[PDB]
């Protein structure tokens, strides 16, 4: 049917951030709806959602997402 | 059949963040609805949703997500 | 048949975060609804949801999520 | 048949967080609803939900989640 | 029916967190509903939900969750 | 200094209130502060602070309030 | 000299309200502050602060308020 | 000399409201500040602060308010 | 100084309101500030701040307000 | 100084409102500011600030407001 496979087989500076905020409003991945049917949110990676957000060397391997929404098939 | 599979088999700087905020409002992954039917949220990775959020070497292997929603199939 | 499977078989630097907030409001993975049928939230990874959130070497292995919602099938 | 499986068979710096918060309000994985039928929350990983939340080397093995909700089949 | 299985067979820095809060309100994995039928919450990992939360080397093995809810099957 | 005087000398329908609440939260005359030096509240009248509040013919006479605060002299 | 004086000397229908609420939050006369010095609240009249608040023939006489705040000199 | 005086000397229909609320949030006379010095709220009349608020024949007399704030000199 | 005065002497119809709301947020006389010195709010009349607010024959006499703020001199 | 005065002496139709709201946000008299000195709000009349607001025969008498803000001298 719906298959997702991922494999990770292996034969194994300065980043300054200076901030100053006042009255910050932040939204990340958002899904606002009204009279819908499904609301699927699959996160395989990273979602950094700061007022001050820093990400370093974040996602290094084998992501796999398989989604199937609906399919009435009457 | 909804199948997910993940395998991780292995034969084995400075980051200053200076923050100063005042009245921050932060939302991460949000899902707002009225009169829906399913609300599926699968996180295979990382969701960092601070006012000051830092992620370092975060996700590094074998993420597998399989989602199948709805399917009336009458 | 909804199947997940994960295998992790293995044959085996300064992080300063200086913060100062005042009246911070933070929401992580949120799901708000009315008149729904299912609300599935599967976390195979990490959800860091601070005012000051730091994640380091967070997710390093064999994440498998298999979600199958709805399925009236008649 | 909803099956999960996981195996982890192994044949085997500085982290400074300085915080100062006044009146912080924090929510983690939240599921708010009215007139739902199921509310399933499976955590195979970590949910760190502080005002000052730090996670190091958090999830490193064989996470398996298999969820199957609804299924009227009538 | 609903089978889970997990096996873990093995044949073998500095953390400074300085916090200062005043009137911090913290929630974690929460599930709020009215007129619902099932409310299932399975934790196979860790939920750290302090005002100050630190989790080091948290989840290192063989997590397996298998959930099957609803199933009217008339 | 601070004088208040009040004299009252007297010589000689249908109310339907149908309410149906659920989880009501009510605050009346409120005063919230930090590091304040004085916090004075004088009520010469009526303070009706219900979830369902009905007031009829409440205050009919000689209210006198004399408030004098501070005076760091 | 802060003086308040009031005198009241007398030498002498259908009201239907129908309410149905759910999750009501109500604040009346509110005073929120930080690092203030005085917070004076004098009420000479009526403060009706319901979720369903009804006031009829409420205040009918001789209200006097005299407030004098601060005066560092 | 902050003076307030008031005198009231006297020598001798259908109202239907039908409401339906869900998740109502109401604030009346509100005063919000940070790092202020004085916060004076004198109410001589009526403050009706419902989700459903009805006021009939509310204030009919001799209201007198005298306010004097500050005056550093 | 600051003087007020008011005298009220006297020698003596269908109103249908049909309402239906959902998620109503209402504010009345509001005062929001940062680093102020005075915040004076005097009400000599009526402040009806409902979600469904009705006022009938509300204010009918002798309102007097005197206000004097500041005066650093 | 700052004086006020007011006197009210006297010697002795269907109105239908039908409303439907969903997600209504209403503000009345508002004063938003930062780093100011004074914030004065005197109400001598009526302030009706509903989602559905009706005011009938509201203010019929002798309003008087005197305000004097500042005057550094």
Image (cartoon, coloured by chain):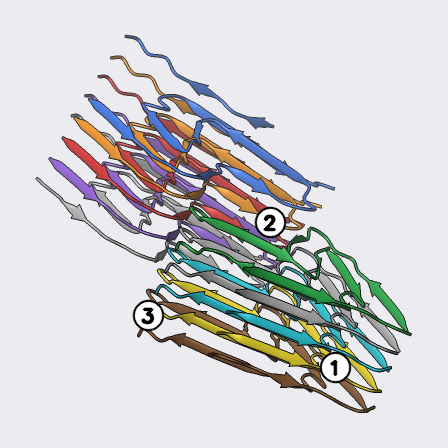
Chain colours: B purple, C red, D orange, E blue, F green, H cyan, I yellow, J brown
The chain ID associated with circle 1 is: I
Relative to H6, J10 lies left or right: right
What residue is disc 1 on?
Answer: I57
In space, the residues marked 2 and 1 are separated at their CA atoms by 44 Å
> In the rendered image, which quarter is residue F58 located in?
bottom right
> In the rendered image, which quarter is residue C10 located in?
top left
User: In the drawing, what numbered circle is on residue D33?
Assistant: 2
Q: Tell me if mark 2 has few (under 14), some (14-19) or many (20+) residues whose alpha carbon lies within 10 angstroms of its own.
A: many
Which-is-in-front pick, marks 3 and 2?
3
**Are circles 3 and 2 on residues that touch, CB within 8 Å?**
no
The chain ID associated with circle 3 is: I
View extreme (top): residue: E12
In space, the residues marked 3 and 2 are separated at their CA atoms by 60 Å
Q: What is the secondary structure assignment of the residue under circle 3?
A: loop
Is any atom of residue B56 visible in this view?
Answer: yes
Residue at the spot 70% in from the left edge and 40% down from the top edge: E73
Q: What is the secondary structure assignment of the residue under circle 2?
A: loop
Which-is-in-front pick, marks 3 and 1?
3
User: In the drawing, what numbered circle is on residue D7?
Assistant: none
Residue B62: x and y in percent read 32, 34
């Amino acid at each position: 049917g719906v298959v997702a496979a991922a494999e990770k087989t292996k034969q194994g500076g300065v980043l300054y951030v200076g901030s100053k905020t006042k009255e910050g409003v932040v939204h990340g991945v958002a899904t606002v709806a009204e009279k819908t049917k499904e609301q699927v949110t699959n996160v395989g990676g990273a979602v950094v959602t700061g007022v001050t957000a820093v990400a370093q060397k974040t996602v290094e391997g084998a992501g796999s997402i398989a989604a199937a929404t609906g399919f009435v098939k009457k």
